[PDB]
Image (cartoon, coloured by chain):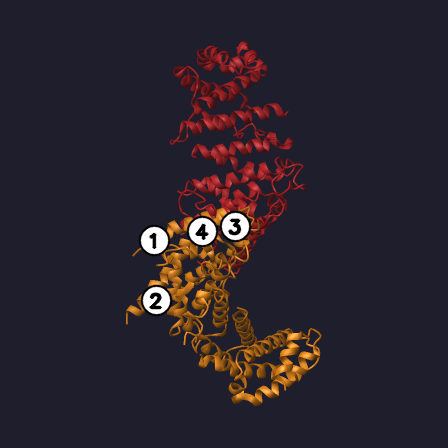
Chain colours: A red, B orange
């Protein structure tokens, strides 16, 4: 709602660099300053415009329809962009050129801004997803994204994360039809998933892979091409940790996201069908090896997330077994782990009081 | 329930020319000894916090006008206090000498801050309280304003002009928005109004200063601190003799009108200055009358209506002066012919109007014999 103002004026947009919106506007040091000042003026104009926001009160009847959880139309926001795209360009203009350490910071800040906007506005979303003639901001992101990932620059750790939070929030706040505009993502998600990437990035890329997998023509963009296939990368990753910080909690977030992805894809309706089960078993044995010893009732939040993941994986595997009856064959390599876990996890879930006919039926099937 | 304070705080045109907005402040860094950068950072965070506060404020308001208290504003204050104490100690030092560009940029910042501060003093009441309430001693922000005013009201600094303009405007508003019980908390300004009123004082600043004298004259204890023996003497020498060679008649007219409203607010309750008031008002009626009459007819201009209104008010005020002093003619002697050439035309005119008042009728009738 109106909270967009509070969000934009959040003192540190990112922890560190102490750069707010103010620290973006008040900078007399692509546009050539023939538009820096004009854009700053648009910025504070839109600040006022939203600080009014007569709209999102007494229900805002126009709020409703598609765009799941209709984002409150904050038209004033539409005026911020030319600034934001000026800076995203000075990042791009500074890129595409075979220092930037400073300019890139303003770009990160502006990306956080755009993130909040896409989060809480609908007119900006209609604009961007509209005109293929993509609103210059979309291209300013995409031509960066490759540079956001391909180059492991010290700051390429963050600009990527923010551009991804933006792309994903924009796929969420919007509707299903426009996603073919997002189509351009698939040329860049692979680099976004390279084992040189950290947990938070692959996470956002998974979330977005899902948000696109809701689209009819988009699911095959998962593994239309059997080779490379924008998968078996996700699985080689989930199995062989390509990150070192690798805070187990983060890896749990990622297992959970990958699981929800697999489930949505399976229910909505590659060579990759084969590796998925191997990776799921590696993951599961990675979980059951943790909680068992602790035993008892999990009072830990991590434990509860793990249990949710395990139950969902069990149901998913039952669906798998429903398919590809060779699943025992492809499982041959790890049947050891599979039968060293399945019985104990069945015991556990039976111990759980939230059991489901699905959980019981599956665990019995195996 | 409105919260327009933020809409006010966010505008680059705050002071035309100076691009410094509230954001050119918050983002202030090492580029620009209690005033260490630590307090800069802390006050900037306080500002952002109070901003988040006011940006959401369901508010429903002896202040004589409820301006819905904006509790969040109170947290915008130490930033202003800091940027003011800077250039306050800076003027203290520029004088202590007996690097000015530092003071220049600094006072630009402080002007921006005084603007933010006047918007607050206007649209909030909790800020009014946090500003007026204090030791007498006094509250540090008010103390800073007053120490500064003297330094800009004195020998002109190229920016002292605007510094003083804004400080006087803030005094005016912090006087209006509050109640009468606290007025005497402003007493300390009677030692320093004169220089805000000196023979070298531009029209806007004096407009503000006399508006302030009239915002103050409600407080009896602060009422006579006119003729002590008399500030009005400077005011009248000014209203009659026109310094500020760069002065649009409209400015002189705003000032004349405010001085008339002042004389009125005083009348509704031993000065060489009180013998001179009449010379001033007579030359003043003559000025307005010679300015308007020749363009006789239905008053179509705005300034025309403004003038004629000033005229009705001045003539009523004169009739008052007469009832006050019988020697009225004795003092008028010096410009008696001005007075007797003006009053008849002013009477013909006042009758020509349809808004005639028994008083403007009686007063204008008694004098014109």
State which mark lies toward you, 2 or 1. Answer: 2
The numbered mark, 2 or 4, whose residue comes first in the sequence reads 4
Task: Please state the total of marks drawn on the protein image.
Answer: 4
Cα separation, mark 1 vs mark 3, equals 29 Å
Give the SS element for disc 3.
Answer: helix
Task: Identify the residue under disc 3.
Answer: A84
Cα separation, mark 3 vs mark 2, equals 40 Å
Task: Using the rendered image, report if marks 2 and 4 lie on a common chain.
Answer: yes
| Quadrant assignment, res A212 | top right
Q: Position of residue A66 (x, y in %)?
A: 66, 36
State which mark lies toward you, 1 or 3. Answer: 1
Q: Chain of mark 2?
A: B
In the image, is A9 to the left or to the right of A268? left
Q: Chain of mark 1?
A: B
Identify which residue, B128 or B152, lies in the foreground.
B128
- Residue A96 visible to the viewer: no
Task: Identify the residue under disc 2.
Answer: B91
Q: Position of residue B173 (x, y in %)?
A: 49, 61
In the image, is B80 to the left or to the right of A119? left
State which mark lies toward you, 4 or 1. Answer: 4
State which mark lies toward you, 4 or 3. Answer: 4
Task: Identify the residue under disc 4.
Answer: B74
Cα separation, mark 2 vs mark 4, equals 26 Å
Vertical placement of A223 versus B81: above or below? above
Task: Identify the residue under disc 1.
Answer: B37
Q: Quadrant of the N terminus of chain A?
A: top right
Give the SS element for disc 4.
Answer: helix
Cα separation, mark 4 vs mark 3, equals 32 Å
């Amino acid at each position: 709602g109106s909270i967009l103002i509070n969000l934009l004026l959040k003192q540190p947009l990112i922890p560190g660099s102490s750069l707010s919106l103010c620290h973006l506007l008040s900078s007399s040091s692509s546009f050539s300053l023939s538009a820096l000042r004009e854009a700053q003026n648009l910025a504070f104009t839109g600040l006022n415009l939203v600080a009014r926001n007569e709209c999102s009160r007494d229900g805002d009847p126009a709020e409703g329809g598609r765009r799941a959880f209709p984002l409150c139309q904050l038209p004033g926001a539409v005026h911020f962009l030319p600034l934001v795209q000026f800076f995203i360009g000075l990042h791009c203009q500074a890129l595409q050129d075979l220092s930037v350490c400073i300019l890139e910071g303003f770009s990160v800040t502006a990306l956080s801004i755009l993130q909040h906007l896409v989060c809480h506005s609908g007119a900006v979303v209609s604009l961007l997803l509209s005109g293929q003639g993509q609103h210059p901001l979309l291209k300013m992101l995409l031509h960066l994204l490759a540079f956001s990932s391909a180059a492991t620059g010290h700051l390429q750790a963050s600009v990527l994360t923010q551009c991804l939070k933006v792309l994903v929030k924009l796929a969420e706040n919007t509707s299903c039809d426009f996603l073919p505009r997002f189509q351009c993502v698939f040329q860049v998600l692979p680099k976004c998933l390279s084992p040189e990437t950290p947990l938070p990035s692959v996470l956002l890329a998974v979330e977005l892979l899902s948000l696109l997998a809701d689209h009819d023509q988009l699911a095959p963009q998962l593994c239309s091409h059997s080779e490379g296939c924008l998968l078996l990368l996700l699985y080689m990753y989930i199995t062989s940790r390509p990150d070192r910080v690798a805070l187990e909690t983060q890896w749990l977030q990622l297992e959970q996201e990958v699981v929800w992805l697999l489930a949505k894809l399976g229910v909505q309706s590659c060579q990759c069908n084969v590796e998925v089960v191997r990776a799921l078993t590696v993951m599961l044995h990675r979980q059951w090896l943790t909680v068992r010893r602790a035993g008892g009732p999990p009072r830990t939040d991590q434990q509860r997330r793990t249990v949710r993941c395990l139950r969902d994986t069990v149901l998913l595997l039952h669906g798998l077994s429903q398919k590809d009856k060779l699943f025992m064959m492809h499982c041959v390599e790890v049947l050891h782990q599979f039968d060293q876990v399945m019985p104990g996890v069945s015991m556990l879930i039976r111990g759980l009081p939230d059991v489901t006919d699905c959980e019981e039926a599956a665990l019995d099937d195996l």
